[PDB]
Length: 187
Length: 113
Figure (cartoon, each protein chain N blue to C red):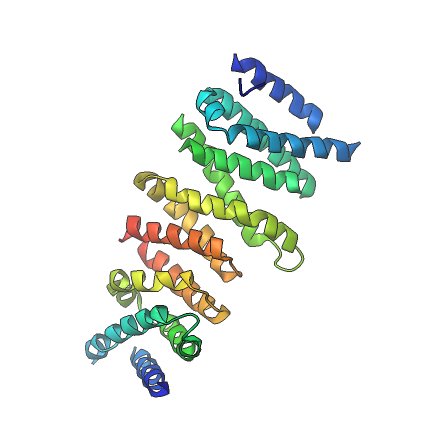
């Protein structure tokens, strides 16, 4: 339906996320709907046609779902919501509004990945690995000024990743981000 | 082959123990640049023995950068950061992880931290 007035759709989404949030059924619908949002906004046409305010409203809904999941657990729904949210917010890079709503999420997700238990949370580490490497590779998309805007606010959080065992994907992502760090700082 | 790793390992370790002061530095930095480049240029599969041979000394070079003062650490930051950053592209052991982590955290501390 939506691949072929956006306020109505956005309002429907907004008013239905409260319904989505017995309990296992609600969690299943929440997972399916965040996957639906992912599969939808992965399309280039709808992404290019949606107004930015409506997209930000959907992203706020997704952040609310992330916060609800985090509050309950402190599982797959939180990781999926974070992945979709952060990936779309890189796809943004109006600009300042999405920028202010993206850096805290990146800091939180990096801190969570670092603080994950290596042995008792192997499933959580596996779940969070692709989204973390996606964030790290998306830092390459930042311009020169924005990359140095949060260098002092993100370098300590990202340096500690290599202390734990890191995969080849995260290896490459970290290598590119730190080479960019050196280039914009000293290089 | 073993002598090449053995001589360099003894050479860099004593020169790190030095930190007259300028003379030893002029004879230490070029060695550290060469050994770091050599370790990366080692073949991962056809030179696994060489990598194992060069592993204990390269991690010894990196840990010695903690012994440099603030001035000397930033003296060769532009001439040594590009050589060391590519290390983590190849598979790295636990020993090199701590050695790399301390120097780059110091790199940020002396540069931006």
